[PDB]
Image (tube, rainbow over all chains, first blue to last red; front, side, top):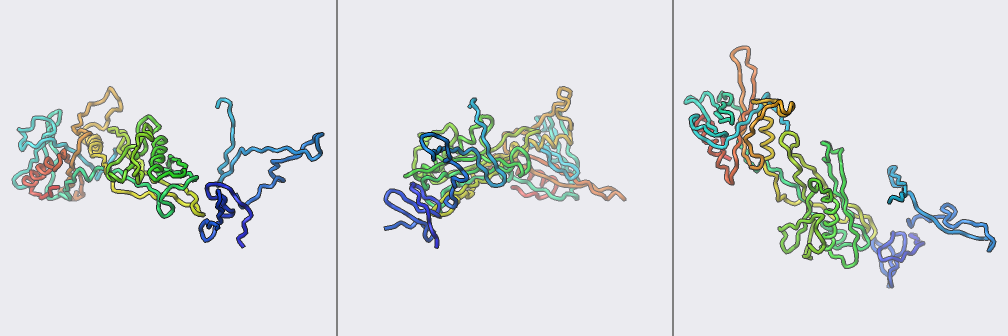
Length: 38
Length: 51
Length: 333
């Protein structure tokens, strides 16, 4: 239900309503953390 | 402000232009001058050449 | 300063104790005089203009007599220990601007409505160690506080390396990144400053403050990046400036209330207290009661001061004499 509709490329984390792209890793705010993806 | 989306309808960063190279002829550009912070805090600008 | 009075107060400096009114030659010499019945007690002071005698104390009418040391009057300078709270992050978070905000409450005005804020900004980087952060932060605070060049910074700033956790390291707007070499820095200390004192018109005041932090973004929430915890003080403004205003005020009950008003057309009053020395004190409170239908009381204090020299030798002798003479048993601080 928590639907994200933005992605942000940056070296510092963006707002939690977006995904976090940084040089080979993407991260989304899950369980009060930025959960990487494998 | 990931919550919002800045509509070009309202900001008009890209607006229409009469021309002869085209009929849908555009023009871009915008500038931020103010910032309205909570509790009535309003910061305008006055650019002085002395500076 | 303008102290409060219970119908009067009076001060007599005691630089020396002579045991006889014939032995009073130089100023500040004092001797406690009491009869053999211990019905009355008074003090003979060698004024710079001669000799004077304190009002006579009916020893049946003594309310309280306590000798207080000098340490009891040395204002301790409130310190602080600013550090990164390991709860949030034990290291600087790159990209976040670690703003610190000093909040001054009693600024020129008397009230706490008269606030004043001095800031400090540090944007972090990759590999920036804690020590490096404390370093740049101290520097930003100094260059923003000490950069008045008039009188004194509103606070003094120090770093401390884990090697010598007791030795402070001053940081002023003249200090440089190169000046600060050690890398085991743990904290930023922010002590408050002894403001200027002027006999009669600028009393011993201070400016209290609290370091208010500003919020950064860790994993997903705004958060205060540090904690400002008080540590035990290590510097005390000495008494000298405090006794001196006492005399300047308590010598208008004996002498002139005009001090410089008609400036050239005024009296020179010779104040016997050195404002750069430490002085113990000895207050005695007593009253006078009439004969008949005049049982109202007139309470009145007599203060005596004596330079502290490590041990309180000057005041303990003065106390011992007043006890053998008056029959009291004032306790030797």
